[PDB]
Image: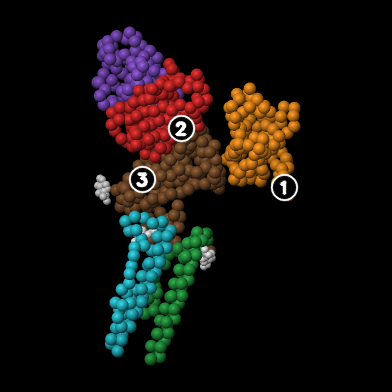
Chain colours: A green, B cyan, C purple, D brown, E red, F orange
Amino acid sequence: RLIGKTNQQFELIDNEFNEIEQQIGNVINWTRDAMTEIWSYNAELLVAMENQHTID
Amino acid sequence: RLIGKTNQQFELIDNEFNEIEQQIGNVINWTRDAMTEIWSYNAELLVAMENQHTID
Amino acid sequence: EIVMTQSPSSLSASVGDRVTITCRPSQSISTFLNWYEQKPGKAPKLLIYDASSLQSGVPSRFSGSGSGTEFTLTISSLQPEDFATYYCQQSFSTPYTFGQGTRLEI
Amino acid sequence: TNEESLRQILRRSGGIGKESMGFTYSGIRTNGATSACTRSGSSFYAEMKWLLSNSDNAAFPQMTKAYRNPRNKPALIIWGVHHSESVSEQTKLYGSGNKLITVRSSKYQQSFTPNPGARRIDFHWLLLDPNDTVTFTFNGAFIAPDRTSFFRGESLGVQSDAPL
Amino acid sequence: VQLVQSGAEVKKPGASVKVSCKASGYTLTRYYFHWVRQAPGQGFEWMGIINPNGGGTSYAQKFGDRVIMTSDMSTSTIYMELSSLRSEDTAVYYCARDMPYYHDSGGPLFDLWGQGTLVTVS
Amino acid sequence: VQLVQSGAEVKKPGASVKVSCKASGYTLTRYYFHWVRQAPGQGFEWMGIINPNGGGTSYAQKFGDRVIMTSDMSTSTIYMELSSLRSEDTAVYYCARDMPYYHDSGGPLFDLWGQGTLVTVS
Ligand SMILES: *[C@@H]1O[C@H](CO)[C@@H](O)[C@H](O)[C@H]1NC(C)=O
Ligand SMILES: *[C@@H]1O[C@H](CO)[C@@H](O)[C@H](O)[C@H]1NC(C)=O
Ligand SMILES: *[C@@H]1O[C@H](CO)[C@@H](O)[C@H](O)[C@H]1NC(C)=O
């Protein structure tokens, strides 16, 4: 059930071996980091829900 | 209850009949798509919660 | 650039005569030769292009053929209208070049 | 130009097939030029001709080229604009004059000019729709493609240091 | 239908000259225009080409940096500016409307010629 | 190993001159090149410096805007263009390959000299 909610197609946005304009790169890094926290929150919450439900 | 959580004011960011710098457009498309998945997740989860609660 | 020569540089001819004028380029200009008619004190006019295709409005007296390094222009049954100086043009490569001119006289 | 977008397109292309533009360049020099690619010998990039004047300082001809897309796949078309180190270098290569390049399709139009003061090749790209014709206008400083590209089967463009 | 040209001019050496031609009838964007010199009893010399669609130009090395061509779409004028005039520049200057026929070489096809402008330098 | 120069030239006043030097052996990017005038029986005059790594130039005010230097990496040529020639410009022009030794002042060290080109203006 968890896999079906995470298994998505991803592509490179950032050229890791090179450089992208820093102003945009800062937006992308900020966006990704913010989204990482959103997904980390969602992940912790979802796992916690699944754990509480498992106990229940 | 669901309507009150979704009914928000929206404006056009992308000029659909024209073109925006592709680097920014890629960020916007990525952002919107990521947010679509976030909201789709939230929507599925919320609906699932409401369905489980309805059954309960 | 490409340098070419016309032959002959001038002719003496009368009405009803047939005239042939040729061009000899330093290198192949496969089909890229135009011919023009110039009247004294006036701008030249296009007669034939691509060494074989007549310009619209040009009378049947004019025709031509050739390829590579040998090109020809022929006029049949000369009229008073046809006594002019004829020029070649090489469209093959830059800078574009023109011939010496061939004049028809009596 | 828009290098990241283009790179991403290739990353998901599935691979590249090549097909000739069918462009005949009579009177135009297309010989090897740069020493930068000496690894294969002193020549320019394998599939894109510099289109230099037939001789040094000679004027570049005003060319019009057109390519119709013969297939149901969109064609990826790349052309370069050569930025010379200085005005004198540009003059030697493409002759004197105001160098202008125009590229047009049914849904695209853009003009370009080289800016002397630094050696560089700027590559620009277009995705040409089926049944359309890409029109090019050359006044010099145009590095023409000999071939175009078609995409085949959804690849994954990974950037990595790991061994296979 | 027609190409017409400005009157003959007299210039001193080292001066500049501007020669104008006006086009009537057809639009300019469909054709390329060339300047060709008719030397005073000598053969034709190509000076250069202008593309009115974007003002792009190309010049023969014989003239090199001495020539600046430009166009005016609002008045239908193709005027050319030649700098650093010399006594050798005395000639009749023609504007030619060239049809883009020779797609193989970008070669000109001189469809319509202008009146010709006599420029004398001395 | 060598710097060699184009042959002597004669120019009229107000004309331009281009003097060429070719470098054989070593690459150009490791050295800076200078142009120095050897006036006809008078002392040396510095004209300017060119950095082939990016074509940057600097000129003495004595020549000011009259001089344009440029380089060609593909042919190993350092040709210089001098505009608005005067009778005072008659001289032997040298290309010098200067080793970047004096890091304290950016001063030149003339490691290798060219043949010298005699330019006569009159
Ligand atoms: C974005 O984050 C990466 C590390 O994930 C970092 O190397 C890069 O410099 C950052 N971009 C900018 C503009 O700081
Ligand atoms: C953004 O997405 C739209 C479709 O929603 C697409 O047409 C557009 O080209 C995309 N932008 C870029 C830069 O790819
Ligand atoms: C492409 O053009 C040709 C012209 O004959 C036409 O027959 C063909 O159907 C066209 N293809 C498309 C997708 O329209």
Q: Which mark is residue E10?
A: none
- Residue at the location (59% across, 39% down)? F70
For residue E60, above or below residue F33:
above
Q: Which mark is residue F105?
A: 1
**Location of residue F29 by image quarter:** top right
Residue type at the position of mark 1: Ser
Report the chain holding disc 3.
D
Q: Residue furthest bottom?
A: A56
Residue type at the position of mark 2: Ile
Percent coordinates x, y for residue F83 in the rendering = 59, 31
> Could you give the CA–CA distance between mark 2 and mark 1, rounded to whole angstroms?
43 Å
Graded by Cα atoms within 10 Å as few (under 14), some (14 to 19) or many (20 or more), the crowding at tag 1 reads few
Residue type at the position of mark 3: Arg
Q: Is residue D161 visible?
A: yes
For residue D141, above or below residue C42:
below
Graded by Cα atoms within 10 Å as few (under 14), some (14 to 19) or many (20 or more), the crowding at tag 3 reads some
Total marks shown come to 3
> Could you give the CA–CA distance between mark 3 and mark 1, rounded to whole angstroms?
53 Å
Percent coordinates x, y for residue D94 in the rendering = 48, 36
Relative depth, front residue between E43 and F27:
E43
Graded by Cα atoms within 10 Å as few (under 14), some (14 to 19) or many (20 or more), the crowding at tag 2 reads many
Circle 3 SS class: strand
Circle 1 SS class: loop
Q: Which residue is mark 3?
A: D104
Q: Which residue is mark 2?
A: E68
Report the chain holding disc 2.
E
Report the chain holding disc 1.
F
Q: Nearer the viewer, mark 3 or mark 1?
A: 1
